[PDB]
Amino acid sequence: EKKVTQSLQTARVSRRKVAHVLWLKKLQDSSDFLQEQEEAARGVAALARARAKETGEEEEELLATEMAKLKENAFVNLPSRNVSVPDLLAQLGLNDEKV
Amino acid sequence: SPSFEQQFLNDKLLGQNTLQFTKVSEKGTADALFAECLESIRHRRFKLDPDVDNRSSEAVEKLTQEERAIAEKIFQRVDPERKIAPRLESRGCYIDPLWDPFKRVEELQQQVAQDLTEYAKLVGAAEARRQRLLVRASLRRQYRMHDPLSEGHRRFFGAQRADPFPTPHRVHERFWDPSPDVRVALKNNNVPISWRDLHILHHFVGENGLILPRRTTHASRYQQRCIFKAICMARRMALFPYDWKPTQGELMPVMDPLQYLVDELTSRYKATGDLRADAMLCVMLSKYPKLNYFRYLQYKAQTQKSEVEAMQQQEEEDRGDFSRLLRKYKRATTD
Amino acid sequence: XXXXXXXXXXXXXXXXXXXXXXXXXXXXXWXX
Amino acid sequence: MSCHRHVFRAAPAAVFASVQRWGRRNNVHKLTLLVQTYEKPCVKRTRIAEEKAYYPRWFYLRYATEVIRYSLKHHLRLGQALDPNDDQRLDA
Amino acid sequence: ESKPVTVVYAHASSMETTRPASSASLSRFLSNLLPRLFLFPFLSPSQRQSLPFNFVTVDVAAEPRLGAFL
Amino acid sequence: VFYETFVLFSKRVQRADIRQLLKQQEALITKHHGSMLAVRDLGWRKTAFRVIKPRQGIFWFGRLFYFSFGANPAAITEMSQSLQSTNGVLRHATVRMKKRHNLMTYNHHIHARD
Amino acid sequence: LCELEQKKRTERAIQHSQDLWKKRTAAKDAHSEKTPELYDGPFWLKFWRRKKRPGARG
């Protein structure tokens, strides 16, 4: 019967990991900076490959230079939330003290 | 022939709450025609009504103060998270529609309106206006005495406040009883409290700035520790005061302000139905598509589906009263 | 009329179940 | 923190009394006296043990005296154990 | 024979019928894009059949059940 | 190991300074084998009290920023020291991301029950 | 008759054993699925000390 019990413990462990994989999926979707950076890296790779035929240069060094430029240029699309929280509360009527 | 709502419900107090007694049907439907016939017949019978039907009895204290206290405690236990109130809009849940005692109120309002218009026809418009003003004054006087569990009732009947028997200040944890607001704050949203919950930490801090003890906060030991940690971290981050309660401008949770605005507008549109909030959410839906509008969209879909179902039911009734309404009793009981 | 009173009694007898709930308790009144 | 009270349509003596009540319920004077002089750790152990043993008794006796005063004021009578099996039926 | 892969297009065109909003623009883009991406010798029946995936559109603002499901 | 960092820049801080600080933090993350997950701006918020930052001045509010990143535990001390050394930053705090109560997931309806 | 009695007893015992196994497995699966409960009651400072028989003989 120990073997049958083992077939049960495998299912119990598997469903515990199924939950955790779902949690990571939510975290990945919430991560937009990572996704945009990966898309930019893919675009840079495509550009380097195109150059590999257009000019026949060292696509490896082209990739290195483009990735260095991307790392330098990161954080150019920072989200804009130039908002005054107390002012927004007052506009909603939830903040009357306005000294 | 101005109705009761046309005459008296434009006042502040009178116009605040206005229950609906009958479904509204657009002109040109069997329901509308039957309602017109009933209104005409009822007006004619009000003309040919006797004196005995308008007999009224003097008002008396419906409850003693101690009995009112007991009733309030029992209602609170029935709904420990919400506040006790006469939810006359949700009335249908508690009292079956066929046994609604407010049909008498509706018909009495109709009769009063008919009486006032006939009086205006007979004596004169100026006297009618005098009487309308006097009736408005009387309704304002009697507005707050209808609720037996309200303070207006006690004030109207001139009853002294109850002097409750002393109870211990230091009791066992088994008997600790928080208020509904403290209860909601402590439960949070089924999630342990974090420093990011700046909208609630003010409850557990005294006016002196000191964190309140567990006997006062009525929190579990784990909740107390979590709240202490949250307050300490918020203070170290300088988003929560050190020597007083947070200012009204510091009560935003640590989150995106636009998501907070969306949440607040959804809450308004659900609790009261602010058309301005609805319009703001509609424009934000397209202007900032990176926020979360699940609850707002779900409520919109629910309302649209209910409208479609009501239209289908009206079509079925027009074709002939179908078994939907009969089922709402028989099938519900059988289930 | 006696027959009209009989009709009213029949309507009151073949009526709904007062409280719309299917609970298991009848409550008295503590008012007055 | 510092308690702030507004003397408006009231007596300065009454406001001072309210401030005194705040100080007493916050133990401000107790802490000031404690910090004015050095307290050795063993003395602190004994003091905290004494307070933790004492104050609940005071609270219970305060509740008892409150009940006594209420009963004297309202001319209440001593209770008798509720006899079970009493029908508790109205004589009407 | 149902296609193995189903693509659901969730929109809220019911909220803004007079105002096109962004949902209408995205719908127009998809309508003018899919037939061009996929070549066949919202969309016409021929295009719907020729698509390799089962294309279904839903309104989260008009289907409360599907809204909570998604 | 996942972490969330909250920073409170002063008014004197600019977008360029914010970008520079984030670049340095991502450099530290990459050095410690991690990866920056997300960055968000939580708007201008008034402080519960005046912040007297020595050799910088007195401030009555700040702009709040947040970034979440997975990195080796050894990176946290370096990141904290760098943020402390940075001048514009008024206050900072780094914590371990939690499964439920984190800004990545528990980000809406924190105050509105319905 | 003895053989038939034994056979019927065997069938009944098989059914009972299968039911018991299903019940126990369901209970333990539910226990595993449930998240660890956190005891949130009072602590045990009173129980730290014990009063045993004093002096010798204890």
Image (cartoon, coloured by chain):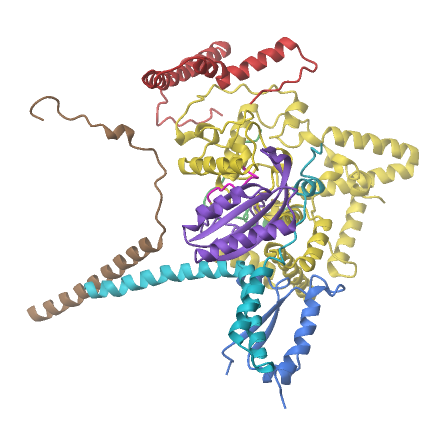
Residue B193 among those drawn in magenta: yes
Q: Colour of chain B?
A: yellow
Chain C drawn in what color?
green
Q: Could you tell me which residue is drawn at 53 percent across and 35 percent down? A: B235
Q: Which residues are magenta?
A: B192-200
Query: Chain A, which colour?
Result: cyan
On the image, the x and y values in percent for residue G26 come to 30, 58
Q: Colour of chain E?
A: blue
Between B304 and B61, the one lying in front of the other is B304
Residue A70 can be seen, yes or no: yes
Rendered colour, chain D? red
Q: Is residue B256 above or below residue B300?
A: above
Give the colour chain G carries in the figure: brown
Question: Tag count in the figure?
Answer: 0
Left or right, B221 with reference to B99: left
C8 left or right of G57?
A: right
